[PDB]
Image (cartoon, helix red, strand yellow):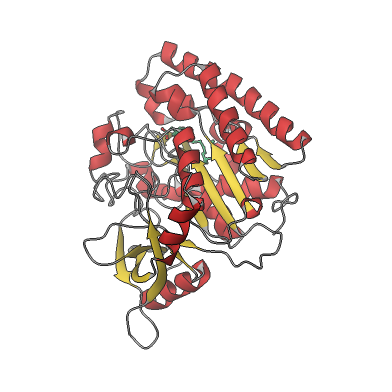
Length: 390
Ligand SMILES: CC/C=C\C/C=C\C/C=C\C/C=C\C/C=C\C/C=C\CCC(=O)O
């Protein structure tokens, strides 16, 4: 994807950069608003990281450093000095106030034990941690009502999984239900796989066998692009073929929840609902066949039935720690992509119960309590990832 000559030239172009530490301003997960501060050292001087920059034709610049994610995290926690359990700290590389949020890749050591040491996420808005946020010039999704480019009031399921295992998370996921395709073109799983393959050729001592891959895709295609079941099946199979041929060995796979149970479908016709629900059911049977196909070949596959979990969550939310599974927490009573540009109050029922008792944050996307509940159910069912080496 990148020539040997291009790789050394980029890696030898050594420099330094600063770290932007982001945090939730409120102690409540009902308030999505965030702010940032520059990372500092305990003596009060600016915290810098050494390394090199690289971007493909896409021009999403990634900073590659030898400094670990744990060290950078610790610097942010110490700089911010918040006694907020909901601070939900995230960090990025940035030369100054004009710079956007660049992901920092912590390069592995040549001496690497045979165990997972990072999570790589592919998919849609159910996994996106901010890939549309820089392109939108930090205006979409509106950072007062959506948590720093996450289509939720906080962390998504991949972030809870990565945190539970104390691993860094590198995100290639990006959705379409919110009109994301008006800000970045190349959002298909195929383009995400190509991007991942391109950026990891610039990483040092990269062993794909030590990556835990998460993949969830198909709802964007069925809901927003009216794609046929065979073409989504073919893309899903192609992503796994491409990844396994590129040394991937560890996967967290999942069935698609019935998206028609989301609040936005209150405004859809029954014919539209029945078409989407039926496509989800055939895709789920193919996802199970694919998980079994790779499992039979000796790959480490964890398959979670999110569909069956979601059916239980919506039929009896009271049994799963929720009061409402039908309505958004935000006071959004239509399905209009322009609503992602504005600040919204919480509807009375959600203001009263708190966002952690609502399944949905907006008309499409689940709350961070739902994301954590899924992440915890995934970790339990796979016995804190029993077939994976940590
Ligand atoms: C594939 C699901 C696996 C993990 C994601 C974690 C939690 C999801 C939990 C419950 C289901 C919630 C909502 C279903 C409704 C809509 C999905 C939303 C967006 C997908 C399409 C897009 O981003 O364009």
